[PDB]
Image (cartoon, coloured by chain):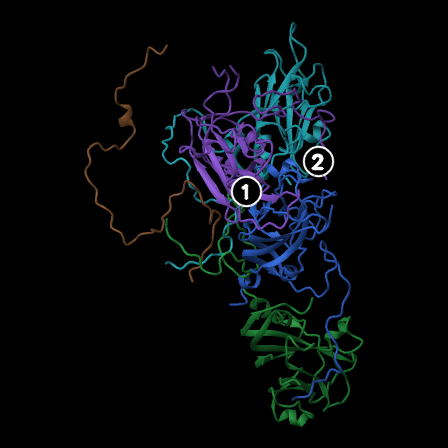
Chain colours: A blue, B purple, C cyan, D green, E brown
Amino acid sequence: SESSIENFLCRSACVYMGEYHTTNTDTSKLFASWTINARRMVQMRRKLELFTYVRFDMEVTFVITSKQDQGTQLGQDMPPLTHQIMYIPPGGPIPKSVTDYTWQTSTNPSIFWTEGNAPPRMSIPFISIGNAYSNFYDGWSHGVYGYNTLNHMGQIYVRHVNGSSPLPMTSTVRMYFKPKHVKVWVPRPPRLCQYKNASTVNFTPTNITEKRQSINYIPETV
Amino acid sequence: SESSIENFLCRSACVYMGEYHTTNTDTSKLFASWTINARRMVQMRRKLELFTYVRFDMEVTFVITSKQDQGTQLGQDMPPLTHQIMYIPPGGPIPKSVTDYTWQTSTNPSIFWTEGNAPPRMSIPFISIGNAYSNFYDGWSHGVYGYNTLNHMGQIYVRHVNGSSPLPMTSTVRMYFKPKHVKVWVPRPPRLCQYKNASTVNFTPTNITEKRQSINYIPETV
Amino acid sequence: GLPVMNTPGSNQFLTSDDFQSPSAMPQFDVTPELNIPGEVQNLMEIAEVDSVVPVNNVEGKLDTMEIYRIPVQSGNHQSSQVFGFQVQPGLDNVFKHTLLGEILNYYAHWSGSIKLTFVFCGSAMATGKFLLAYAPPGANAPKSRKDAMLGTHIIWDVGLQSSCVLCIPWISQTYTSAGNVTCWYQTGIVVPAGTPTSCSIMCFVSACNDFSVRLLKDTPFI
Amino acid sequence: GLPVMNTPGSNQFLTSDDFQSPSAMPQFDVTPELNIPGEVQNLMEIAEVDSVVPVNNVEGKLDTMEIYRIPVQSGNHQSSQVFGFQVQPGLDNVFKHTLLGEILNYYAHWSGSIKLTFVFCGSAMATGKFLLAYAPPGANAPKSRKDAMLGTHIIWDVGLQSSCVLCIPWISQTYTSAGNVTCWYQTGIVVPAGTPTSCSIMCFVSACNDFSVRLLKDTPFI
Amino acid sequence: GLPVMNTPGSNQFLTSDDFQSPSAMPQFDVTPELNIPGEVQNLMEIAEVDSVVPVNNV
């Protein structure tokens, strides 16, 4: 009953930790970004490789902290900061800067939040025109091996909701991920190799198990 | 079921971002102001131009942050700040300064709020002596073309609720807008032109679509 | 009294929430509804209307009415091709800005079936034959009139019918991997004396009853 | 209205909580389920499958197929030992990476009973006898064929049976304090003329119906 | 006990709200009502009375 599929997988984990600033000279360090694939968190990856097709809902909680730079200016009296967290479905537009029009589009679901309150949280349905996600794919996209276009699940963008010419602060986000209502099909043998990259199944040859003294060896009874 | 009218429109967006101070030498930089028309947020504008007459309730949430100026004075121990948010119906008085008597009138609904708490929120009914709002009007006011007097929906004013001779801080407000219980009539073709101003339907002539090589051209099958 | 326990998620502002809200004008009776003709419940009611396709989208004629006319020429040319295109709404420039095309670009995944309609706009004394051929997705475009006859086709005799309707079943999105439609001269156009020389074909596209859309997003047109 | 009292535990994010969550895409109809063969409800369905044991895990043969073959030698050796090991899954290197072993390393406490199966892979003309002996946990390994005969044993005649199955009741975890299994030459292998010399034994391990696991943990393999 | 979840809008003071409030004088019995003539339920009762118009406002 503790070996049920739901108790084995319905558990939370930190999957991404990014940093983003209020003012900078880089314009890519002004927002935080993460493509959502289930092959780049090594926590849940090996537990999912026991199965061939999976189907679940997704629940995401956010933990956000800030600090003021140690550059020059003290004596401030700042109000609490506001943060925007935008989810893009598979097939939506992608921003390029924090001042883009794409932060304001009516079809990207977004969350606004101010510090001191409870941490924010939203839930995602099973978003696939297919009938299950695919942990394994033996074939081509149309041409990249192993990758198909049915495992698109979206992206996450975070920025500050300041006005104009803000004060210099730097923020950090932790994204916590959790699957719900999980169903699996076609079990597979476990991975007896260390993972090399986050896209393929490539590996180096490793031994089957560890050695002992002889085929008759049994350690002494205490 | 995702193409229903309610799922297509009942979604939130930031429509205005203003800034206002506790003490200044301008007296118009001491409060924040926004006339509420549905032709100055480009998010919801193009989605509304598919219809001729609309009818909805309105829900508005506010996100407010503050900071202390970097001018001279540090070592402060300030209490949390209070903010006043006043809605004026169509046909109410309008303030001219923050010290005006019109901030205290019994018929403008107002919200008082202090920082650290949950963000404030109020709801508005369908306020029109007509039976629907008008996205399009072919005629005169009585004389401005395209503008009638049945789409008056009100204004929003925000200031600080300090005492006398306050400390210098500057605040920022984000207004989030969301329509509810939406009903539409008489569909229209979409807008194949970039919007020029926020009052008229003026434009420049653009091409119907994009070109290709010939009338027989089909790209190669992969 | 009544012991109570705050759960996490308290005092956050989530952009997609659906809570009750306090009304700012409770002593207000709204105007009653009026039965205006033309009420819309669903965006599929807009997509299921015919609209004219700009098939002749070649260089030079993109801002004239000549973009909508397919140029049937006179003489004896009884094996040549009249037109051809892939059936890919939302992506291909031919179908991109129609009434069905503009609705499909608010969604990230869609699938259904399409109705095409062809109309011969010549004089009443012209007669001749055309061949309308359909290749499924995956198959190549035909290169002659003979191998188009060996597929799925229909022979359209404009002396007996002014219009011919065509339903296409398997439509979705993700160098095409899509179906296509081509038209071939079977005979050529025969006229009497004292008639105009050239003739034209127009094309209308619409959506059949079953059409599904998912994952509302931002539109990539403004 | 409705007086309410916050209990401690409010506005915390607990990683193991099970609360409702706001959905970010409510206007979205998910793809219906498909009846894929091979659905899994429980991880005991993976542990109750036979898998091949790498018994010959000695130095030199850890990356060849020779690790799986027990080396039966020819001649007259009718008192020597063929093999021996302790029955300790999850800990011992023999059973560590099987299908039952990999599942047991996700749990901290487990207990059940094990089924072993031995298969003689020789030619059809070979005959002989073996003795398979089991000592309970606490008892020492036997040192001769005679004192192995005085315990719990079984005499396996490979000229009449190609396989022999063995169930072991008392299995758990915490210089062994575990049971063990050994195999002894009763007779020796007798062949006719024109046969191969050596022969091999293979071994399969699985779990019986009653098997319990508790306290899900991290796996110590990656 | 009784798991509970705070929604946004908590601990704000909204000027138009209609909540219960704690009374500061619970051990107090108010004076009973007296039937005074001329009770008003509605401001239309004031508008539906004749009043004299200042027409000669030159």
Q: Secondary structure at mark 2?
A: loop
Q: Secondary structure at mark 1?
A: strand
Above-or-below relation of B39 to D65 = above
Instruction: Return the x and y of residue C67 as percentages of the image width and height.
Output: 66, 20
Marks 2 and 1: same chain? no
| Residue at which label 1 appears | B63
Question: Where is residue B201 shown, x and y percent of the image?
Answer: 58, 21
The reply to whether dot 2 and dot 1 touch (C-beta < 8 Å) is: no
Q: As shown in the figure, which amino acid type bears the numbered disc 1? A: Val
Indicate left or right for E23 with C38 as reference: left
Which residue occupies 21% across, 31% down? Answer: E38
Asked whether the viewer can see residue D41, the reply is: no
The one nearer the camera, A7 or B154, is B154
The image quadrant that residue D147 belongs to is: bottom right
The location of residue B188, given as percent across then percent down, is 53, 25
Image quarter of residue B70: top right
Task: Give the letter of the chain under mark 2.
Answer: C
Which residue occupies the foreground of this view, B167 or A38? B167
